Structure formats: C-alpha cells, structure tokens
Image: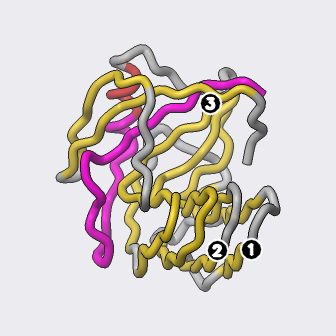
Amino acid sequence: ATFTQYWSVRQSKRPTGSNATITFTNHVNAWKSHGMNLGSNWAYQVMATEGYQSSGSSNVTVWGASTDYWQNWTDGGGIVNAVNGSGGNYSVNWSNTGNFVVGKGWTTGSPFRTINYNAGVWAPNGNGYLTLYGWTRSPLIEYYVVDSWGTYRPTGTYKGTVKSDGGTYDIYTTTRYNAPSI
C-alpha cells in the first residue's frame, strides 16, 4: 500500500531511566497546523520498540490501569525475542532482524491520549526507535513520536517544530510505496 507517515522526532535522544510523558494532543495539533490530518478510523496505539536491520535490547513499561493492547509484529527476517511482561512491562532481544514493532498500549488510538513510560533499558545496536506508534484509516496513516533512537535519526520532508514535555521535536512527512500495516 501507498501512504504518508507523520513524524515527531526529538532534536536529541531523550534520557531513559525515569518516567517520560508524551502529551499526544500537542503533537496532533502541531501536525494539524501544518496541514497534516489523521484518519477518522483509529487503529492500535503503543509505546513501541521499532527495529530494522539491527540487533539490540530494550525494556519498556507503560502505565495505565487501562492499557490493554499487546503489539508484537515481525516480518520474520531476523530473530526477535519479545516477552509480554506483567502489566505494561515488556522486553525485546532482537538479532540481525529486518522490520519489527513491539510495544504495549491501546486497542483503539485516541487523539487525546496521554502516556507515561519508563524505558528501563534502551540499548539498540543498529536501527531502533523508542517511539509512540499507531495507525489510522481514512486516510491510511502511520504516525510516529520518537523520543530516542540508535544509529539513525528518522528524517524526511521538514515541516516545522513543536515543544512538548520539556523536549523540542522536529516535524517530518515521509511516504512509502508498497507497505502494509501492523
């Protein structure tokens, strides 16, 4: 499938060890102001560990009484050890993988969501995103809010900036031709 991607990318890798907050409504409006609108149909929404052509290790925890969804996907190109921890916790040991997404969040995404998380460990050795991840339909859109990464910072068509949660983010739009979902 062909679709546009929305990006919020910190101007510097965010500290990992204490609880971090992603006020999502800030990124949503900032995207709206630049003509970037999400779909009317909301898919899942997680604080995930996105990896590609890399190996590493992560340990994330997502707090909520109400977090229900468990996301564990992989195009089966490499080895991916994803353990569904207790509560909102989870870990990932990936090796020479291709693409994959692992995170815990919500079955249905909300443009008003508020997220507290504690990256117990962020040791990506290659390409890996410590990002808030989710999709929407009508239009079909894959959105990102990246706080940290590995060897590659996600860029694209620059559209502006937004200050949120004591951190400034660069805004990008990218396009993919022949990408699925999940």
The image position of residue 60, as x and y in percent, is 48, 74
The span picked out in magenta is 1-27
Magenta highlight on residue 4 = yes
Which residue bears the numbered disc 2? Answer: 94
Name the N-terminal-most of marks 1 and 3: 1
Q: Outermost residue toward the bottom?
A: 86
The image position of residue 15, as x and y in percent, is 26, 68
Q: Amino acid type of disc 1? A: Ile
Q: Is residue 179 left or right of residue 93?
A: right
CA–CA distance in space, label 2 to label 3: 26 Å
Q: Is residue 22 left or right of residue 181?
A: left
Which residue bears the numbered disc 3? Answer: 141
Quarter of the image where one finds residue 97: bottom right
Q: Are marks 2 and 1 in contact (CB under 8 Å)?
A: yes
Q: Amino acid type of disc 3? A: Ile
CA–CA distance in space, label 2 to label 1: 6 Å
Q: Is residue 22 above or below residue 57?
A: above
The image position of residue 46, as x and y in percent, is 56, 57
Which residue bears the numbered disc 1? Answer: 79
Q: Amino acid type of disc 2? A: Trp
Q: Secondary structure at mark 3?
A: strand
Magenta highlight on residue 13 = yes
Q: Is residue 124 above or below residue 181?
A: below
**Residue, x 51% and y 64% (percent of image)?**
126
Q: Is residue 108 above or below residue 38?
A: below
Q: Quadrant of the N terminus?
A: top right
**Residue, x 42% and y 23% (percent of image)?**
157
**Residue, x 32% and y 72% (percent of image)?**
16
